[PDB]
Amino acid sequence: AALGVQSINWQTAFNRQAHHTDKFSSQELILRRGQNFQVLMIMNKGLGSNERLEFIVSTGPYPSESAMTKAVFPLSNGSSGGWSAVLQASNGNTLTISISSPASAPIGRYTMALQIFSQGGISSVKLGTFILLFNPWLNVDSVFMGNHAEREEYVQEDAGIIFVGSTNRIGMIGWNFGQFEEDILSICLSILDRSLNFRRDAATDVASRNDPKYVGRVLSAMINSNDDNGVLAGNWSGTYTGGRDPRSWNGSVEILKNWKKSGFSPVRYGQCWVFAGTLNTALRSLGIPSRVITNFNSAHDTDRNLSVDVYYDPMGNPLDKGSDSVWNFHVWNEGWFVRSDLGPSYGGWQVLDATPQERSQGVFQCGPASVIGVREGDVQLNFDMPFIFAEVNADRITWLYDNTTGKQWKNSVNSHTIGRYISTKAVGSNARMDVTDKYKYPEGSDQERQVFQKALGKLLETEEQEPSIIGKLKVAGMLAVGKEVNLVLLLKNLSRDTKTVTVNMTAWTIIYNGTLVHEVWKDSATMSLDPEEEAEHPIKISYAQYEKYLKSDNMIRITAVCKVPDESEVVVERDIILDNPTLTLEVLNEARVRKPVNVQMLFSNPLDEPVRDCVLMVEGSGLLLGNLKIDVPTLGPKEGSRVRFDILPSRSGTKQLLADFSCNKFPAIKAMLSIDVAE
Amino acid sequence: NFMLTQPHSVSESPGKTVTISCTRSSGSIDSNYVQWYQQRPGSAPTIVIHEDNQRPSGVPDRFSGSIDTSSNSASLTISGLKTEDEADYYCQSYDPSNVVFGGGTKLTVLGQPKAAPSVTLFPPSSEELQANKATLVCLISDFYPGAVTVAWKADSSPVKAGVETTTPSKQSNNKYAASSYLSLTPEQWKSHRSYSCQVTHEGSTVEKTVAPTECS
Amino acid sequence: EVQLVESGGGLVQPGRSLRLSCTASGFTFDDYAMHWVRQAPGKGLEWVSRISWNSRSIAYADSVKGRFTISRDSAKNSLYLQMNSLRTEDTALYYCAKDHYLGSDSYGMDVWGQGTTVTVSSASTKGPSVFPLAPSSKSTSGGTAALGCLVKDYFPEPVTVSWNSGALTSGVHTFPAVLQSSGLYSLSSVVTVPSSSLGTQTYICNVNHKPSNTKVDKRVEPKSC
Ligand SMILES: [Ca+2]
Ligand SMILES: [Ca+2]
Ligand SMILES: [Ca+2]
Ligand SMILES: [Cl-]
């Protein structure tokens, strides 16, 4: 015949193992750019000497050789930059062929065809398709990450930890990233095919998928619903009718599947750690090494001056006033790549944030921002550095406002409080790794103030005597939903005179971002104090008082505004978090791959009332497929539930089982169990 | 829009495994989640699979769902069949507007010998023709499992308008029977060379034929 | 547990209107989309309509679009279906169904009510006309012959049929009825007998329709030609 191809062997399993893509649950050939793969191609005869083959690869709807979304390359003896195919051996009619892409190739799905020149004729045959990802193993790839252990954490690990809580009590939730789970890589690639950029100009978008800066910024937009019907619809209202309480999610898997299967319609509802977990999945799936960051006391600066305003009334109510805010924490991501746009001192970790806060070039997106650049205060560099710098290091101004007079006055400036205990999961363990010193110079240093002035640069008060009165709120005993709250306010008089202190106190339930929900308690007190006398004032809030307005955040904001005659107010502030009841998971046998293992959940109702509508949701990559739901019967007061269920480990290694227990009185109780799966 | 096509019926013996397929006519089966439902006679449907392959609380682990991209189909698989699994089963999916159900599959758990239907096709009676009407009556008896499909032909061509078919029900002897009717005008009856009733049972077809020139 | 209770079903004439109601309890009503699905007797499930959790997105089957309107009411935890311009084809059991999905626009029916029955017909009470299904000319003796009665155009159900006043029971089968597009029911009854009996044993079906207070006898004769 004319020379024609009979069959192709992609040697998928071998190539996937060599390309570090073997973990994805998928049949497809998944490869990493800049790295060869070997195929065997069986022809109808041996190659004639007036015969030639060309490979053609293309990605996207408008492939172009000049944009590098199409390449045409001969089967040669040599590699010549770009894409190449080397005939490694002929044996009969079988060709052993090593194909390789350039390190600068666009990521995504590709088609491969073969063009045959034979007997003066030209024929073309589609060979197959493959997925090409970024290559953090390859020294010349922009996403290169040289350390083995760190690549394992930041690319290959599908279970993680996100720090939450407050500066008074840092806690953690597990998160199932689940980048290897069925359809997740495919869904993450679909994200790119649905952005506003792709819809506007697919040819340019696809060509730009060689750039982790670009893919990273696209994902920061597309993970939020705003503008583009992307993945997650945000809600910080405390009312989650029509969707899941943001705290009930345990991973990215069901979110991404629910988006796709609904016809790419937003999933309801997310808060910041939910956006971050989901963005983390997408980054790791596409091969940008990434991790999740939590910033405590995180500032939302809306007017680009690196200062945020918080307001109280003289009766000690927090006020919702001014666009700016301070969150108990905010979660975002870092991606690992060089910054060809900024230069060599600014590569490494880059902030990316899918939480819709500020528009950037018209669109709710954020980053990439060099972490190094933020610490040095080079806030003129792309992208979104003013906003990010304020999040970790705004100054905070406390104001009194009295709407009866219309007067506002400045109480205090606090230049140390924003940006604390910036945290990420340690490599290879669940320890908390503090990265504040990467984002800022130390609080209290000359450097920190110098950098603040520099940053400010790029984008009358009378100081009174030191207050006579100092105060602080302290917790007495346990904080637990169902139990009363006991606090002490401690005041001390440092002046030389006796002082009479008038104290106005409130407690407000809040969302973790500072959204005020409802007042649940308020008192006033008057305390006469001798020079140097310290005194206490007990504060008691019953279950009945908070039960109706406490949200899944379990947060109460307590405030004491203290005043003596002829001195400015002192504001004493404490946010508390109440513990959920204990929820435990245990495995009753050792976990071995492919063998069922019985798990046990224990939960005790601490209330004197029954709990109803009890649901256990469980998931964990490598331990079960998808999300198990178990209806649990109504629990009488002080009664315990014991629920047993099987799981079926599918991979060996250290895996993470997550559970959410929800009922009418306790939304979103969380449990996590590390499970060692043996071969 | 799309359709979901299921087999009319399936059967297997107690303790064996059976599979019911659900093929999507256009668009990808994995674009949207698939559910399965069981329906017993006299009762509302109950859900047995949701989200392609998840099992509700209370459903035995003998029930499983799957998706097969290559055939653009979903499947419900029941292992260790018990006599109580005999029921109708429906698949369901959706697009961003509309909900689509499969046409249903009767699952028989085999408890007696398979038995081919006996078919009798009656032409219109002279009494009916004298009342200016015409009904062809195809009576189907003595079969098992209790599932058939009925196709009518005018000459050698399909006809569905004016057909009504009963769902099979048990006879005294514990086999099944069914009926089907073709309503015609006397003019249509007298005009055609012949009409046929074709009954397909367990992949085999029985046909019977009547002509207006036979009772002459 | 979730309970859904439909009501408002009944007999009604083509072109008139009917309103169905469904009361929901045992879950947070406003969290979920709700559906109507219908099933004609002995047939398949046909989705009718969906309404979103917040009532802002509604969809209809093509077969009902323009004629039916879905709605819901939060304070009464209820779903409704206003059905106008009814047709005999709208005859079905109408089920209320809670959607499975929380927080996404996918659709599935996690809980179904027992349904409310809707019969659409212009018919008045009417006794049947009975026609013979005469045994084949080609009665191979040393074999069997089927013969029957066609019991046509009655309303409402049911009809019962006996043969030879209950003297003939062996081989008898009386089929379920069909509802015709006219709004009237028909059924058939068949008996299998020895071919050698046809010349000498008389065969009469006795049809009883209690709603019309009619009993109708029909003699079923072998065909001459
Ligand atoms: Ca968006
Ligand atoms: Ca500001
Ligand atoms: Ca600072
Ligand atoms: Cl606390």
Image (tube, coloured by chain):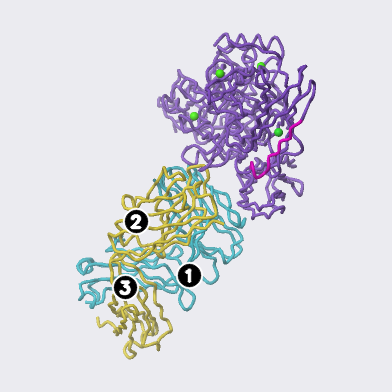
Chain colours: A purple, B cyan, C yellow
Quarter of the N terminus of chain B within the rendering? top left
Depth check, front residue: C213 or B105: C213
Instruction: Say if the magenta span includes residue A34.
Output: no
Do pointers 3 and 2 mark residues of a single chain? yes
Q: Earlier in the sequence, mark 3 or mark 2?
A: 2
Q: Which residue was labeled with disc 1?
A: B144
* Number of marks in the rendered image: 3
Query: Splitting the image into 4 quarters, where does residue A301 fall?
Result: top right
Front disc: 3 or 2: 2
Front disc: 1 or 3: 3
In this picture, residue A490 sits left or right of residue C195: right
**Horizontal and vertical percent for residue C149?**
32, 79
Depth check, front residue: A525 or A136: A525
User: 10 Å neighbourhood of mark 1: few (<14), some, or many (≥20)?
Assistant: many
In this picture, residue B43 sits left or right of residue A484: left
- The segment highlighted magenta reads A536-546
Rounded to the nearest angstrom, the CA distance separating label 1 from label 2 is 40 Å
Task: Give amino acid for label 1.
Answer: Tyr
Instruction: Say if the magenta span includes residue A544.
Output: yes
User: 10 Å neighbourhood of mark 2: few (<14), some, or many (≥20)?
Assistant: some
Chain ID of residue with mark 2:
C
Q: Which residue was labeled with disc 2?
A: C83
C186 versus A436 height, above or below:
below
Q: Which residue was labeled with disc 3?
A: C155
Rounded to the nearest angstrom, the CA distance separating label 3 from label 2 is 23 Å
